[PDB]
Amino acid sequence: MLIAIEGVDGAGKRTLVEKLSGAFRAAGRSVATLAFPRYGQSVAADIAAEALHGEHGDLASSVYAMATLFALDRAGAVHTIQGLCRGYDVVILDRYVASNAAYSAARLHENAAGKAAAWVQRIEFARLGLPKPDWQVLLAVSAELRDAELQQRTGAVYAELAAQGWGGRWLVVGADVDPGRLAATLAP
Amino acid sequence: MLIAIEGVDGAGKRTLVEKLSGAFRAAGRSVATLAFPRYGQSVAADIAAEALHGEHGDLASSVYAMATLFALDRAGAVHTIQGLCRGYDVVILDRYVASNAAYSAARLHENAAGKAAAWVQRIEFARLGLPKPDWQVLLAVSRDAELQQRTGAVYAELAAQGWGGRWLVVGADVDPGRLAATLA
Ligand SMILES: Cc1cn(C2CCN(Cc3cc(Oc4cccc(Cl)c4)c4ccccc4n3)CC2)c(=O)[nH]c1=O
Ligand SMILES: Cc1cn(C2CCN(Cc3cc(Oc4cccc(Cl)c4)c4ccccc4n3)CC2)c(=O)[nH]c1=O
Ligand SMILES: [Cl-]
Ligand SMILES: [Cl-]
């Protein structure tokens, strides 16, 4: 089973991943985790990070150019993801394809029903063949939570993506989620 | 030996590659050829081509975003290039790294000594590890018409600077047998 944990930076995804992993293991389920972007492991991810810090000329000014680098980062991990899914009962990804839909739409002042969100789904799931997650868990935070307005808009798109079932089933949870009850909901 | 053929669209690079290959083969040396971008074989190349036709949102509006895709296209061919260079006497590339310097600078309205050109050399040769060509042949002949003119001038500037290695500047009626003899 493939589970994606989603949310804006600072939401607390990492702690939720650890909480859910322990809950899964406590129930007898093996767990592996993988975090995107793979900074320090993917040239596409590293070029993106560097672009965000003002390097590589005007690269960061293109929303779709940045989204493509993150998509290419995941496309190189597809064999890794499949291997984990074959060896572990649950695979939890800290950020996945929906991250591209949320930030790309937010950067372009669009909503989950907009072009950018639909473009991400087409290119990552349809063309590049990335496995669709069985679950996408949105760790939701408020508007008050670098660029503060971008994170707020990204948060709103996230909720819309979840409400629309973008790419599969979603769960909307808060920070202090009940780990045993959540693992039971995800893996019955 | 690694040879790159450079020039603006319509210069006749494809024809020169074919003529030069036969000259090399006629001289008893094996030849393989590879054309960039690898449209239809690289996701980065296809996304770039599609971006140039108005798809993929704002991707084409970024000079460095386009250059990065062409660099990533070549970066995915780096082992392919190395394999061919180890198996054939001559490897001729239709377009290579210098294309990124020329079109990026020309789009930047900057000369070969500008930032983009130095950025292309840095990211493709140093960082991405693309092999430096033994020869870069500029087919010097002259759809945004003003963009192509600037790209041609930057091309000649790159050749004058020895950008990335030795260059040869040739015209339309170049003698392929004499050119193959000069290269090897
Ligand atoms: C996995 C993924 C992630 N993201 C975003 C990319 C932006 N970060 C935030 C971020 C991340 C940044 O760079 C970082 C942040 C932390 C560590 C490193 Cl090494 C680099 C930024 C740097 C400068 C300015 C703003 C920055 N903002 C959140 C996930 C996408 O847009 N699409 C994706 O597919
Ligand atoms: C290999 C390489 C190539 N180029 C350029 C990219 C642009 N083309 C010209 C071109 C190429 C285009 O797209 C094509 C053209 C022909 C075939 C395909 Cl599949 C796509 C264009 C489409 C619309 C409008 C203008 C277009 N211009 C010349 C090589 C670089 O800038 N850097 C590179 O590294
Ligand atoms: Cl977080
Ligand atoms: Cl040509």
Image (cartoon, coloured by chain):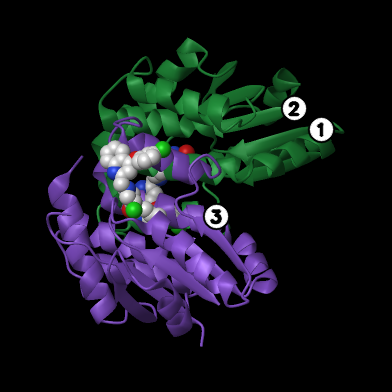
Chain colours: A purple, B green
Task: Give the number of the mark in front: 1 or 3.
Answer: 3
Answer above or below: position of B69 versus B139: below
Instruction: Say what secondary structure mark 1 lies in.
Output: loop
Q: In the image, what residue occupies the spot 27% across and 29% down?
A: B108
What chain does mark 2 sit on?
B
Task: Give the number of the mark in front: 3 or 2.
Answer: 3
Report crowding for label 1: few under 14, some 14 to 19, many 20 or more residues within 10 A (C-alpha). some
What chain does mark 3 sit on?
B
Q: Amino acid at mark 1?
A: Asp
Residue B80 sits in which quadrant? top right
Answer above or below: position of A65 versus B178: below
Mark carried by residue B42: 3
Mark carried by residue B1: 2
Instruction: Say what secondary structure mark 3 lies in.
Output: loop
Q: Earlier in the sequence, mark 3 or mark 2?
A: 2
Q: x, y percentage for residue A157?
A: 21, 67
